Amino acid sequence: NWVACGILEGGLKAAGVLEEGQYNRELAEAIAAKGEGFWTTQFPQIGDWNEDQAAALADRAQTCGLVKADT
Ligand SMILES: C[As](C)(=O)[O-]
Ligand SMILES: C[As](C)(=O)[O-]
Ligand SMILES: C[As](C)(=O)[O-]
Ligand SMILES: [Zn+2]
Ligand SMILES: [Zn+2]
Ligand SMILES: [Zn+2]
Ligand SMILES: [Zn+2]
Ligand SMILES: [Zn+2]
Ligand SMILES: [Zn+2]
Image: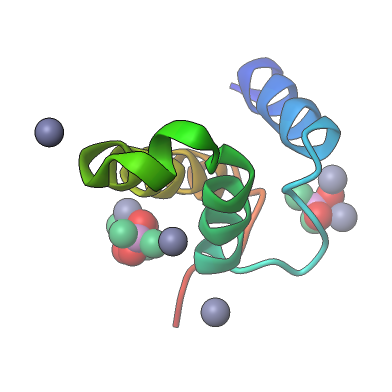
């Protein structure tokens, strides 16, 4: 619903990953970049988790109509 999607929108804006006219792929990339840190650099599995969760979150953002579908 709009409330859940709005909370998601606000949070992503506040985290500095969501912007205007952004495609799903771009949002996912921005989230993964902000998720990088000591653990993603040291362990492949953590780096993969970061990318997979980022993609999943961007997907939820798209469903919430916050980003454009990849074409
Ligand atoms: C794995 As994707 C960026 O098509 O949701
Ligand atoms: C299901 As999709 C539009 O995130 O590849
Ligand atoms: C159209 As919008 C989700 O960038 O306010
Ligand atoms: Zn907006
Ligand atoms: Zn806008
Ligand atoms: Zn790119
Ligand atoms: Zn990467
Ligand atoms: Zn391991
Ligand atoms: Zn997806």
